[PDB]
Length: 28
Length: 95
Image (cartoon, rainbow over all chains, first blue to last red; front, side):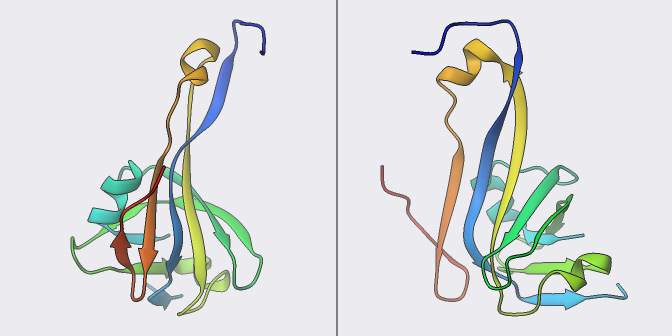
């Protein structure tokens, strides 16, 4: 157990897992 | 930055213009940018501008967003996770 507090947490909202880059465009 | 198939954004719960972190399994690089929508069904992951220095075509990456909330809400929070196979084809997640 972790005791309850009044503070704001930063939580992972969601992720793309091991997606592959298709394009790389330095100038645009 | 990074343009992402809108279907992928929705599946991970990430919004257009939301801050994202990108962690590159191929080269180790870690950077932060924001999400641009690419056409639904395009299966695009495009690193643009300065972010082109952090990945190349073919690199395998994790793209994440983070949110804030109170401690109590955080205890039952469930992240969205989208999994992929082959050529960026989305597959179903297990438990």
